[PDB]
Image 1 (cartoon, rainbow over the protein chains, first blue to last red):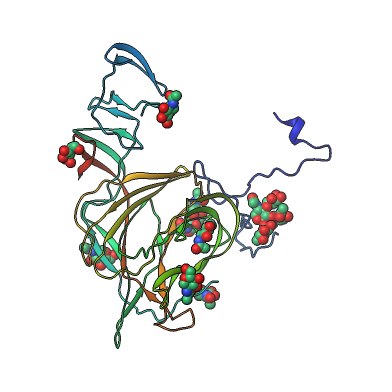
Image 2: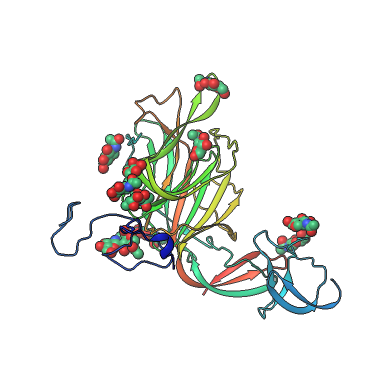
Length: 49
Length: 49
Length: 278
Ligand SMILES: *[C@@H]1O[C@H](CO[C@@H]2O[C@@H](C)[C@@H](O)[C@@H](O)[C@@H]2O)[C@@H](O[C@@H]2O[C@H](CO)[C@@H](O)[C@H](O)[C@H]2NC(C)=O)[C@H](O[C@@H]2O[C@@H](C)[C@@H](O)[C@@H](O)[C@@H]2O)[C@H]1NC(C)=O
Ligand SMILES: *[C@@H]1O[C@H](CO)[C@@H](O[C@@H]2O[C@H](CO)[C@@H](O)[C@H](O)[C@H]2NC(C)=O)[C@H](O)[C@H]1NC(C)=O
Ligand SMILES: *[C@@H]1O[C@H](CO)[C@@H](O)[C@H](O)[C@H]1NC(C)=O
Ligand SMILES: *[C@@H]1O[C@H](CO)[C@@H](O)[C@H](O)[C@H]1NC(C)=O
Ligand SMILES: *[C@@H]1O[C@H](CO)[C@@H](O)[C@H](O)[C@H]1NC(C)=O
Ligand SMILES: *[C@@H]1O[C@H](CO)[C@@H](O)[C@H](O)[C@H]1NC(C)=O
Ligand SMILES: *[C@@H]1O[C@H](CO)[C@@H](O)[C@H](O)[C@H]1NC(C)=O
Ligand SMILES: *[C@@H]1O[C@H](CO)[C@@H](O)[C@H](O)[C@H]1NC(C)=O
């Protein structure tokens, strides 16, 4: 636990996690892309909505 | 200790036996040698090489 | 920076037979006078291997082949190279060769060896280039057109400086370099071997076990790769940096590894001298 280091009174937002990936990651694989995820059938064009 | 029956711990690999000078020429990336029974029968000394 | 080459003659792809090449040491365990059976990603014996040329033969039509296409990286790549003037400069591996995804660059800058996992905006026609000076009668490296921008990365490695003479030797191929590239569990496995050899056109027939070269902790998704070559410029073949170039004679062969069981023979000296594809 690192609550005394990685927590801020107003909220520490410097740590991020990847959500909405097309497929599961392979072992020891890193994905740092920031492309907009397409959950529905409507294509995205680099914008969120 | 050579030419004597001793317990040996070579780079974490433990065993018992007699160590003698070997004519085998290990490749630079190789550390252990095994026979047809998969037993460690040759070893490179980590210090004297 | 980004420059696309022109005046390239269109020719059908070439295919050759890999007889027994592509065998590498499965592990780092010494074995002597044994027959060892192991299941691993191997190049099948007598496999259909793609062949790419780099050659400029003059004439009314001639042939100007400078082959650096983007080839698939399915499960592992056997890359053989027959050359005499060090034409092959390196490779780039990735999924989308642009800034969207991270890519691995293994290049020879004619002074150091650069291995970089970085977000590269690769050119459509990436290459390297040396220049021949009539007064000096020497070849110097002058062009590096692999990528446009590099950003958002982790992996950097620069080798010790060397000379790596760039003279345009003429005659027969005097170097055969074999590489095995694998991408397993976030690790880029590179096995390498070098052979003198002496022949004209095709891949030499024989056996040569590839020894482990490097274990890069890469950790990226790889499905495609492109070979970065070196072109020649001099007082001849004039142009505007897009058509004023000549390609030194070289060939490189690409094959794909599959999960196979191989029976290798370790001689009394611990060298793999023969193999059987079960
Ligand atoms: C991934 O790249 C982002 C863009 O880098 C900028 O653009 C490049 C083309 C190049 O010119 C480079 O020099 C620039 O700095 C990094 O910056 C973040 O980009 C996001 C847009 O997706 C933006 O919202 C952030 O403000 C910006 N931050 C900074 C400090 O520039 C990324 O940096 C990291 O990711 C961010 C989400 C943020 O957490 C930032 O603090 C991080 O350092 C790069 N990501 C990496 C390196 O993981
Ligand atoms: C590694 O990259 C390949 C290609 O970029 C990914 O395969 C693609 O997967 C998407 C869906 O996930 C498909 O729509 C594409 O058609 C696929 N392309 C190819 C060439 O196969 C693969 O999913 C990636 N692997 C990981 C673990 O992210
Ligand atoms: C330390 O190990 C090296 C092997 O790299 C060896 O050459 C050297 O003799 C060793 N020194 C001592 C004091 O044992
Ligand atoms: C090379 O061709 C591609 C075609 O996809 C083009 O996008 C790129 O701009 C060209 N490079 C140049 C003109 O330098
Ligand atoms: C190799 O494959 C190509 C097409 O992929 C085919 O034309 C050629 O005949 C094959 N080689 C052999 C020896 O069958
Ligand atoms: C190749 O790159 C290395 C470091 O990236 C650099 O030191 C070297 O000078 C380069 N070689 C050239 C530009 O010919
Ligand atoms: C010849 O070599 C010298 C140093 O090696 C270099 O400064 C000079 O530019 C070269 N000649 C030409 C025409 O580039
Ligand atoms: C094994 O090594 C010895 C000594 O170096 C040599 O005489 C012998 O020819 C080698 N065996 C083979 C098959 O090369």
